Image: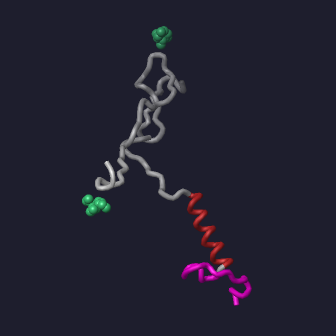
């Protein structure tokens, strides 16, 4: 009850954090590890697991 | 109103849900006014004013 104190909203909302996580997930599923070291190179998932 | 010989409400620590002791008794809420700080967004003096 506003007793001289307040909370500030986080700069990134929950929706944007979820979007970041989903982007990381899609990158690590459809592009293996190379998407974190330059351009994202597609590769079939069984070959990535190999 | 809630009970005769005890009427001054307070929910957690300081809300004090009563004026002090109205002769009409009975209580609604407590929120006269409540406001916070300010901040200024500036792009830089050497860029604009
Ligand atoms: C006057 O006192 C009586 C108490 O029963 C009640 O009507 C009220 O609390 C007070 N004010 C008015 C306008 O009657
Ligand atoms: C502001 O911008 C101008 C033009 O880009 C630059 O010359 C100057 O060093 C900058 N800083 C200040 C404090 O003026």
* Residue nearer the viewer, A41 or A30: A41
The percent coordinates of residue A34 (x first, y second) are 59, 83
- Residue at figure coordinates x 36%, y 47% from the top left: B39
The percent coordinates of residue A40 (x first, y second) are 61, 78
- Residue A1 versus residue A37 in the image, above or below: above
* Residue nearer the viewer, B40 or A39: A39
- Residue at figure coordinates x 56%, y 62% from the top left: A17
Q: Quadrant of residue A32?
A: bottom right
- Residue B37 versus residue B9 in the image, above or below: below
Q: Is residue B47 left or right of residue B10?
A: left
Q: Quadrant of residue B37?
A: top left
- Residue at figure coordinates x 44%, y 51% from the top left: A8
* Residue nearer the viewer, B24 or B48: B48
Quadrant where the N terminus of chain B is found in the figure: top right
Ligand 2 in which quarter: bottom left
The percent coordinates of residue A10 (x first, y second) are 48, 56
- Residue B36 versus residue A24 in the image, above or below: above
Which region of the structure is painted magenta?
A: A32-50
Magenta residue check for A4: no
The percent coordinates of residue B42 (x first, y second) are 35, 51
Q: Is residue B2 left or right of residue B23?
A: right
Considering every residue shown, the one lying at the far bottom of the view is: A50
């Amino acid at each position: 009850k506003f007793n001289g104190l307040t909370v500030l909203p986080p700069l990134l909302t929950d929706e944007m954090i979820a979007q970041y996580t989903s982007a990381l997930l899609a990158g690590t599923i459809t592009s293996g590890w190379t998407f974190g070291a330059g351009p994202a190179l597609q590769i079939p998932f069984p070959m990535q697991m190999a | 109103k809630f009970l005769p010989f005890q009427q001054f409400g307070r929910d957690i620590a300081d809300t004090t849900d009563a004026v002090r002791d109205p002769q009409t008794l009975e209580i609604l809420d407590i929120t006269p006014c409540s406001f916070g700080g300010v901040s200024v967004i500036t792009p830089g003096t050497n860029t604009s004013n």
